[PDB]
Image (cartoon, rainbow, N blue to C red):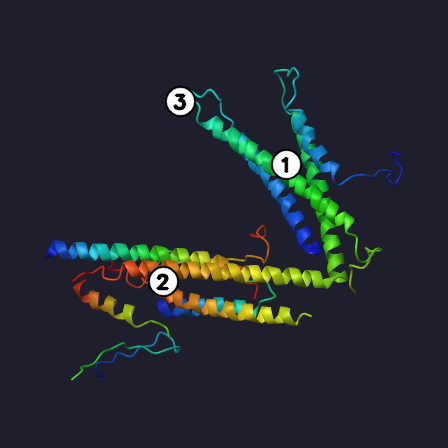
Amino acid sequence: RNQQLRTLQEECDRKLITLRDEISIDLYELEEEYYSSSS
Amino acid sequence: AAPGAPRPSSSTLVDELESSFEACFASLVSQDYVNGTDQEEIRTGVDQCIQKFLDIARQTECFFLQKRLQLSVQKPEQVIKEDVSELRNELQRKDALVQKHLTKLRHWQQVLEDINVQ
Amino acid sequence: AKHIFLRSRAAATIDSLASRIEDPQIQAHWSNINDVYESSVKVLITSQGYEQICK
Amino acid sequence: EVNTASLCRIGQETVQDIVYRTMEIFQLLRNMQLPNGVTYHTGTYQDRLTKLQDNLRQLSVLFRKLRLVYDKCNENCGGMDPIPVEQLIPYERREIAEVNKKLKQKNQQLKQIMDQLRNLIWDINAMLAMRN
Amino acid sequence: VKNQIISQPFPSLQLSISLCHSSCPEDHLYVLEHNLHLLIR
């Protein structure tokens, strides 16, 4: 059960890090688009 | 007409660019004997050719800005249409990027729906 | 304290753009790894329609 | 029908890109190592000369477009034939305004979406203290 | 006083996140997990 829950939380943390990376990519790419707006 | 003020010449701003460009490179590509001893010699010439090149470039660019300003103060409708087209392109690009990000986030959250089977 | 301070800083930065539009705008860039207490924010002048003004 | 402003912008962009291409090709042919490499038999120089010819074609068509747009500009001399140079030193647009307002509304909406995305995207900074 | 711990670094906002028995800025979820884990830490 220990190994089960550890693998579960490890995959959860991996998915969270991947989502963080995706969100940061979207943000940084949109911030460049945010500079384009001259208003 | 070396000390004279007037410049008796014409036909420039077009041939000058290619001339200056090919000038200090023909020195390189040449089917002629090259003495195997030289230092700090061609450097002066290449600095001169790049200097005159960037100078005439600056001249052309300043002429372009002058013409553009005179056109805008003459025909502002053209500048207005240009700005409208630029704004349309910017809005289209923004919408495309927004749709792409939305689709990416959708695809991402969709596959990690039941990651925890439980 | 850190949370409310970061919030106020972000608010001030984003309001700066609204308060001054004709003036050179400001781009916003935050880090990708922010510690519990430590964090960093990248901010550039980013003069409009030019890329050679990053001084 | 005229697009003279866009023409001048394209010409400026083209000459700037020509200078950029010159710099790039100089940086490229800068590290022109010995073709008869000890380890590399025929790998590098092939792609090197390929990119060389590519940049050559690029600068050629750039010069062509420059000449074309210059001829177009110098030929279409319509409006202000005198063109006073001393007229540059100081002492309808409804559709334009509507499009500007629409773009500003879309920008504000996108900014609100991005603001929400900020909080929805940090997501690790608050809880990295015990994350694994 | 009772299940509430009010505090102020400086007079700008409120504090004392808390809970109770049964029978916008998303500063709601990631404020409890930290203090929760603090005990096991």
Check disc 3 and report the residue beneath it: D39
Numbered label tally: 3
Amino acid type, label 1: Ser
Q: Which residue is drawn at 39% across and 65% down?
A: D117
Output the chain of dot 2.
D
Task: Give the image location of residue A4, x and y in percent.
Answer: 13, 55
Task: Please indicate whether residue E29 sits to the left or right of residue D13 in the image.
Answer: left
The reply to whether residue A35 is visible in this rendering is: no
Task: Give the image location of residue D123, x and y in percent.
Answer: 32, 63
Q: Relative to the observer, which residue lies in front, D112 or D79?
A: D79
Q: Mark 3 falls on what kind of element?
A: loop
Q: Which mark is residue A23?
A: none
Check disc 1 and report the residue beneath it: D60
Output the chain of dot 1.
D
- The image shows residue B11, relative to residue B42, as above or below, that is below
Amino acid type, label 2: Ile
- The image shows residue C12, relative to residue D17, as above or below, that is below
Label 1 in the same subunit as label 2:
yes
How many residues crowd around disc 3 within 10 Å: few (fewer than 14), some, or many (20 or more)?
few
Amino acid type, label 3: Thr
Output the chain of dot 3.
D
Quadrant for residue D92, please give it. Answer: bottom right
Q: Mark 2 falls on what kind of element?
A: helix
Mark 1 or mark 2, which is nearer to you?
1
Q: Residue at x 27, y 56 (%)?
A: A15
Task: Give the image location of residue D112, x and y in percent.
Answer: 45, 69
Q: Which residue is drawn at 59% across and 52% down?
A: C53
Check disc 2 and report the residue beneath it: D121
Picture quarter with the C terminus of chain B: bottom left
Q: Mark 1 falls on what kind of element?
A: helix
